[PDB]
Length: 376
RNA sequence: GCAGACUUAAAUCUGC
Ligand code: B12
Ligand code: SF4
Ligand code: SF4
Image (cartoon, rainbow, N blue to C red; front, side, top):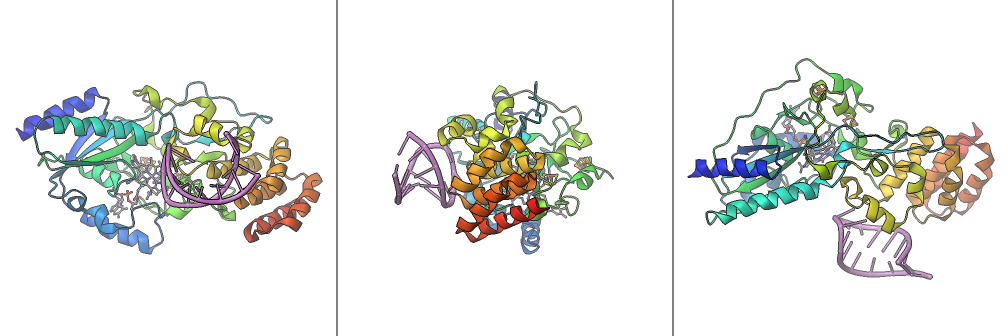
């Protein structure tokens, strides 16, 4: 009965494109609670997580009388077919692989909906509660306890066949399914991810200072701290460094889901056009990727910083207009700072003009930084 | 229609 239901669920999940499925109980996540209290007090959290620790570690609070959790994982592509070349006149930014093609929030919500349907179509009264990323549970904690993959040193859940390049989701049920056993650590004495992290956000194996992680920094809506502006490169959203150096990901390039295939012109887009983009054109072109959940502003800020990184002089006119006309303090100030960074002294007069008119205190400071740079 | 804010992609509010 319960065993047959479990095998039928696994059979259906694979047919609708789930790459890996696993089972765990609805027991509380005790070690996780202690861990979350630790990270919180160390200031190592991001603020993006659920504030209520009880709801995060107690499945039976989320779904009354729950008895199990079904965890699913989908592998996403890692290599890009015919990536467009970034030249001196035409510089390009880059999205992380978790932001290629169709938003996994929607892809995996679909798989969870079909699996909720499947169970509810058989026995009653099977009750469920699904979630992907935006739920209370820790998708990694569930995936680990369900045997999807092991906790690697880069904090990533890593699977034997697909590596770390997988999306995670889970469904809480009232079915007392038989749980699986967690898989073993494959990292060994390797430390490549820890050593290659540009900001040392990986303070220890399996421990992240989220405030120092590039991925987090690309999604903040305010001014990017001076400390990290030199380490973003041309990233527009997220970071893949602790994964692309990982030996467990060598050869892992799976094209199993067509809608996840990146559009090279929007995954690796031209920087300058992003600066003058309209809301409709952004919604049409970027509105269906995961990296647009905070809006266009963090992406544009990063695009500016990316141009400063490249010292693209051809971006100076658009940056200048942005400094003068844009109603967003973060955009004005960053444009001012980038202008000074690119290093053309001819634009110094324009910085002073902007300075004399700025009313936003923080934007003022960024202009002053930009002026100081151009003197040098 | 355009733009901004906000929580988060269409909802709410504001400006043209
Ligand atoms: C907040 C958040 C972030 C934050 C911080 C992530 C972090 N490491 O804490 C930021 C914005 C930086 C981020 C970045 C990324 N994230 Co993110 N993020 C989340 C989110 C919403 C919650 C994660 C969280 O609460 N972390 C807090 C820590 C404490 O817990 P946890 O890592 O989830 O759980 C593990 C630890 O607690 C550990 N642990 C427990 N006890 C102990 C004890 C010891 C001693 C140690 C060492 C560890 C340890 O074991 C748990 C299970 O592995 C989840 C979705 C979700 N709802 O769960 C996605 C999620 C974790 N992110 C994901 C992705 C894809 C990424 C990025 C790769 C995106 C990118 N390309 O930039 C990067 C990777 C950066 C990295 N190396 O961690 C995937 C991870 C998939 C996978 N294969 O593991 C998730 C699961 C989203 C999803 N639904 O697929 N993200
Ligand atoms: S995503 Fe980038 S910044 Fe964050 S821990 Fe990994 S390598 Fe470091
Ligand atoms: S780089 Fe090495 S230590 Fe880091 S996750 Fe990959 S195998 Fe593990």
